[PDB]
Image (cartoon, rainbow, N blue to C red; front, side, top):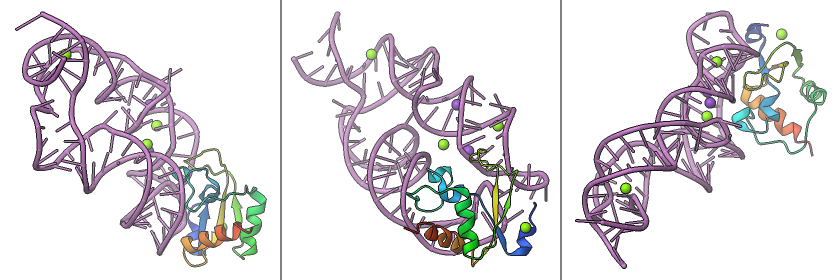
Length: 92
RNA sequence: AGAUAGUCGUGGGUUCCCUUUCUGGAGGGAGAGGGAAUUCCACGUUGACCGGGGGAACCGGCCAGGCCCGGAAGGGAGCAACCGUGCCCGGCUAUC
Ligand SMILES: [K+]
Ligand SMILES: [K+]
Ligand SMILES: [Mg+2]
Ligand SMILES: [Mg+2]
Ligand SMILES: [Mg+2]
Ligand SMILES: [Mg+2]
């Protein structure tokens, strides 16, 4: 799906950003104790009106295991966005 | 012509896992701190040097392929191979 997003205030989220067992392996923020399922996630994104649209047929290089990828709207910066999602994920 | 043994300190490098600031359409970019290693560099330090050889899938570094993101460039996690080490042989010197 190329780079359009750039023009849509979109940014790509590889699920690993959150649910990687090791940072070197991909996590960019504190580990999430609980375990989180895919659909649950999406859900949360939507919940923050990030209007997630998913992209199948896309393999993270640090684990070709994951074949999909989520497109989301930047809230302020990919960064802020993530914090926000993560922080939200740790919803007790 | 015997037995063994081959300096320690701080700084930094790197690597591993962790926490963290800013950031891009991916691979990612620019920083901060903590801990655990080090086979890697500083000088300073000590009698703690000199050569030789060698090869771990399961050690460390690195990584052809293959598996990936990229428009490409390139960037990645990573197996074999390679390297480095581990090891072995002398001398050299040290304590018995
Ligand atoms: K290897
Ligand atoms: K690499
Ligand atoms: Mg789109
Ligand atoms: Mg490595
Ligand atoms: Mg390759
Ligand atoms: Mg000897």
